[PDB]
Image (cartoon, rainbow over all chains, first blue to last red; front, side, top):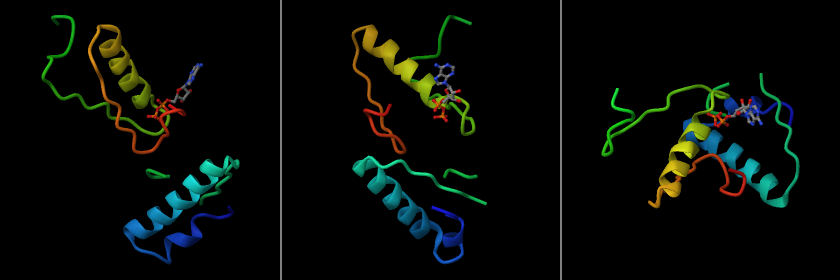
Length: 43
Length: 51
Ligand SMILES: Nc1ncnc2c1ncn2[C@@H]1O[C@H](COP(=O)(O)OP(=O)(O)O)[C@@H](O)[C@H]1O
């Protein structure tokens, strides 16, 4: 996912974190390796 | 002094990503489990099997 910083502008404080956590947990459950590039906080 | 924190106490393992906070907490928990007591680990960023 290149870059996960793009979604910072288009979203509120908690909604962006919720979206990123949703994707992280989805890839985790399906077992996929998850590379995340960012331009770093609790992330 | 005295050899440990007070029992009914609060401890704050402040740090940054990569410091080892979770591992120090897990060591606290392992002490509790090895001495016959029960301990709880509330993870908010890690699966239990992953931990
Ligand atoms: N076998 C090992 N030898 C040396 N260091 C290790 C080993 N396993 C893990 N670590 C260290 O543990 C750290 C992770 O600690 P962690 O409990 O995840 O801290 P936090 O959760 O606060 O980021 C890493 O920085 C890594 O260097």
